[PDB]
Amino acid sequence: ADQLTEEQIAEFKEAFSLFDKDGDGTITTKELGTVMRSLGQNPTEAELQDMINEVDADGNGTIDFPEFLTMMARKMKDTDSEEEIREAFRVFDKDGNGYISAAELRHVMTNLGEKLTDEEVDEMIREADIDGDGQVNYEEFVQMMTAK
Amino acid sequence: PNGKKKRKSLAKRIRERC
Ligand SMILES: *[C@@H]1CC(=O)N(CCC(=O)OC/C=C(\C)CC/C=C(\C)CCCC(C)C)C1=O
Ligand SMILES: [Ca+2]
Ligand SMILES: [Ca+2]
Ligand SMILES: [Ca+2]
Ligand SMILES: [Ca+2]
Image (cartoon, rainbow over all chains, first blue to last red; front, side, top):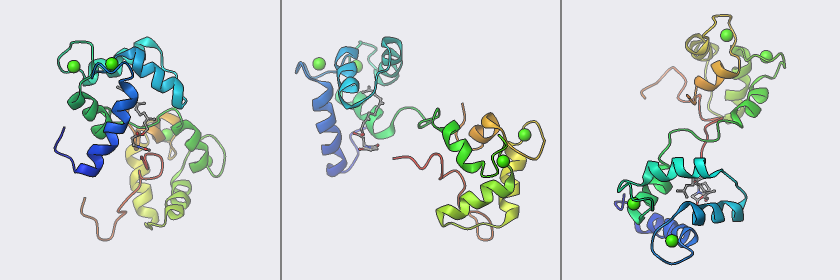
């Protein structure tokens, strides 16, 4: 994971310095939870464990630089917020019926600046429309972009 | 992905990412 550029390398160091408060050179869930609690997040020990065992390739219970760097640079997981995706759902749902149709996503894509025709939007709905109603609900809209 | 006359993006809204 060390094959990054010096700049990016410096960033995670500063972060590693946060996660290694005892100064042993490794991260545990206790140090992790401390950082989380400091910047404004509070996952439980099990959730802490989850990400710990993800990056911990030695399976030794502590996160080393390369493992941390994997979590930090690669993020380890493929998703992002996920739970706020249902908040963003209402944003795409401009008509406000609890479903997102092509026309709705069409407005939203235009809001990004990158234009597309209605057909490209319909294409997206065709693939994400699991119940085949011509609209996408939470899970359809979610898995349209960020899968579970 | 290669797209000339099709959407170059779509997912960039909710997974805009950091
Ligand atoms: C904003 C967006 C981004 O990616 N970065 C760079 C990385 C960074 O330092 O962001 C702040 C880090 C946070 C909030 C923690 C993110 C990691 C987790 C929630 C997983 C924790 C697992 C560990 C520590 C093993 C920005 O600056
Ligand atoms: Ca430590
Ligand atoms: Ca380790
Ligand atoms: Ca709607
Ligand atoms: Ca549907």
